Image (tube, rainbow, N blue to C red; front, side, top):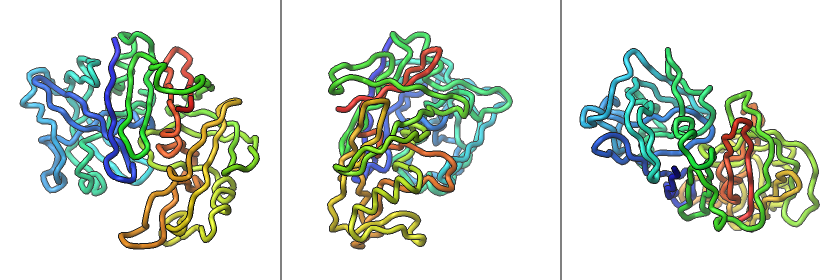
Amino acid sequence: STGSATTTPIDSLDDAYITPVQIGTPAQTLNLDFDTGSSDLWVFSSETTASEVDGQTIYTPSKSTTAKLLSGATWSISYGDGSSSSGDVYTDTVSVGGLTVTGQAVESAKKVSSSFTEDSTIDGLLGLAFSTLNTVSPTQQKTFFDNAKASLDSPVFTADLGYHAPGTYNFGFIDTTAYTGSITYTAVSTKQGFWEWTSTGYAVGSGTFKSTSIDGIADTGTTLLYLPATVVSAYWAQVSGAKSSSSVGGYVFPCSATLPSFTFGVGSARIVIPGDYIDFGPISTGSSSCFGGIQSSAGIGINIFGDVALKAAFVVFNGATTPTLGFASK
């Protein structure tokens, strides 16, 4: 089997991407944030505290003839940005882009933190990291991909995120028309439960490539590119007037600037992030100070190849017995 679904930016900055997911019978379609940095499929629901729902579409398990309460199971998650959610668990039929899993754990939120309430466009998350990170207790549950894998034509999924435009998540096949050149594959460590890999270096603009190992995670659920402070300083030094602002919480730059590109290495291959992808717009409405899309990972404890990086590539998440990642230009 295969599946293919379009993923759409939630706003004009590409702060996140939403993909429609069919849950239950008859189907209830919710727009979920596909997150290769976590491993829970959780949704706003008829059980979510009413004051914590503000415009999201909810899953109502009592209206699904295939929903079954997973007796005694609870979940609770906290994300790297400080947000969190928790609740109980159903199993139900879940379909993405024509690919159907029966008996998928659907984690129904009883509580969500304010950042989720305040974002009316995201109805929940669909985790695509390794199932070892799943938070369901006392019986850990499998991700959608883990449940689908054995049925897929090939045990892979691909992320093709758009810049200021929709893109595609495919399951079970590699669309050879979706990229240019070749896909360069690179080793993955699953020891922390992430799609963790080592970039071979970077360049700023037209500058020389610096060969240096940068361990980090491929994370579709993180907006920005978080790299070591040395790398980030080297980038922003090429933007007149850019500086790190402690009060804003990162590097800012004059909105009048033209940003240089940023290149990262995948083996001997190179992925070029155009400068425009690094502009996240005014820090507050009407400001002439703009927020940068490349930020320091110092204090986060891991480097994160988030959407800023991934949207410059066609990315293969190869879930074979020994997982690997693939990157192609596009």
